Image: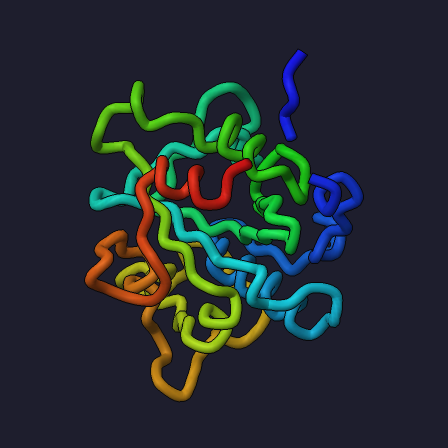
Length: 203
């Protein structure tokens, strides 16, 4: 026997609609997460400041993520980058919202790290994950994408675009690379190693 602990956790009500009810485009997770933040903002359930956009990437833009819908099986999807929503409930328990995961939506933080992320120790160094964590309030206010990264030299779509106009701010129409970058001298929020990330938000 072992005590694994979270009263606020046990009766947790999701901040999102059911998985099938959410706005979703494959290979546009940065926008998928943005739309989850917009929903949470417009609904008066949770404060936006309890929520974070999490960009997962590295120097070489090759990060393995397990339990992905794209490749349903044992082995991982290798992304250039991936974005999920992290909700730290007032009690201090963390939940992951990943529309691309075969894990539950939402999923307990420790469970998502355990099955989807795993440890960076036994992983070839060039594949190791870094995490950029941005306040959902900050993400909604500052993120902009013209989707120019998703169209080839001929100007054709690599993947079909989301069915709504490009997200832009007063300040910029495209700053995606400042979120994809795991250079802490660049962009918004904080850049964390795997251990820093799991320690800060983990049970």
